Image 1 (cartoon, rainbow, N blue to C red):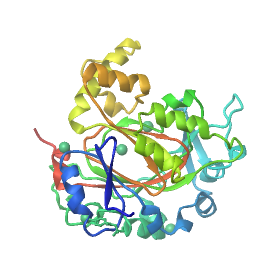
Image 2: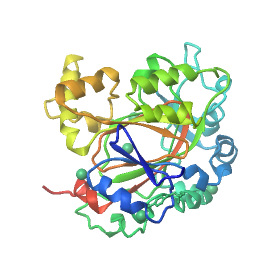
Image 3: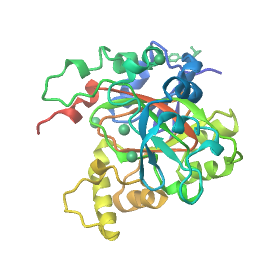
Image 4: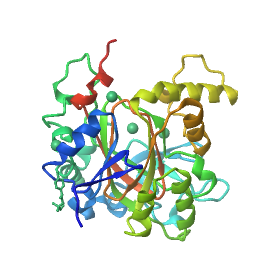
Amino acid sequence: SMTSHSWLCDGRLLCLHDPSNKNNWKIFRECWKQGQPVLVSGVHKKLKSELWKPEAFSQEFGDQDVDLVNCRNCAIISDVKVRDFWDGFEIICKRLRSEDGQPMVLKLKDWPPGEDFRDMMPTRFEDLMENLPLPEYTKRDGRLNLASRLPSYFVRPDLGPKMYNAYGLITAEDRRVGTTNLHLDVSDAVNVMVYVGIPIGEGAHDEEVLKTIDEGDADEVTKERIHDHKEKPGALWHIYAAKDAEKIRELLRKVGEEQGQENPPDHDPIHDQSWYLDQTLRKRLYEEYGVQGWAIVQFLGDAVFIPAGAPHQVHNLYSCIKVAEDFVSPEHVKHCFRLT
Ligand SMILES: CC(C)(CO)NC(=O)Nc1ccc(Cl)cc1
Ligand SMILES: [Cl-]
Ligand SMILES: [Cl-]
Ligand SMILES: [Cl-]
Ligand SMILES: [Cl-]
Ligand SMILES: [Mn+2]
């Protein structure tokens, strides 16, 4: 039967089921005030699916110049055409190859660039902004979004949204790599999975995806969305409470020293955006520092709410198109204040 919500991460994560329900705020706001992330499913059913396909982005914008990142080694591929990324999104025999002759796992950097999403893609902008969940928090002029209402004593987010496009990580060695490394934001954010591309060529890659989710610490109910409902999984997230950020910095300073990095005692390994917490590091954070996180699988049409100050990392299972909007809730405005 249809219900309003469920609890994932062994009861520790709210999952809303109706993205446009006028009463969602009554369930949301208590979890949000406690500094927890929230998942909202079903946003893909509200969108115009023809606007969010890789072949359309290639046809309309393919002649623009961009830089890519090689996810495996962080090498920058400079000044290529954006069609060279899009045409390899799902079809493995079209991907740029490294010198070993293997197809690369690539991330499309800063595209559309800076604040240009609205100017470059006005119809996509309308379709996304009109269908964001919790609109009093997430719309540019929502009553509970302080972004447009704060003086210069607060760090204000750029004008959004921002698009995040990258291929899926494939191999057993790839399990230790991030799509986006561990970092934090001083604003709140909502991140929507608008498209998941499951390839063909090296298609039959189902098995390494299940081992990644299982070793990723995903709960038993999350494993049921695959086997029972056949939903498309996009990306594995780990999110940590804002209150645990300094304990994470202590672990990463100790590990940086063990690995012969030579860092001053005060340097900030989260701001550096240079670490991915693999199974070994996540277990060491729990056992040695007492810190538990949330392991979240973001399926097609899931919106992940990330609280200001919360350290988080992202590992794509398949090729993903994500679109994110920043906002400033009253619950978490302390995180962007420039004094004390
Ligand atoms: C039978 C329906 C309406 C179909 O979606 N399911 C619900 O109960 N939805 C619901 C979601 C949020 C709130 Cl706050 C209230 C109700
Ligand atoms: Cl907080
Ligand atoms: Cl458009
Ligand atoms: Cl709302
Ligand atoms: Cl990164
Ligand atoms: Mn982020």
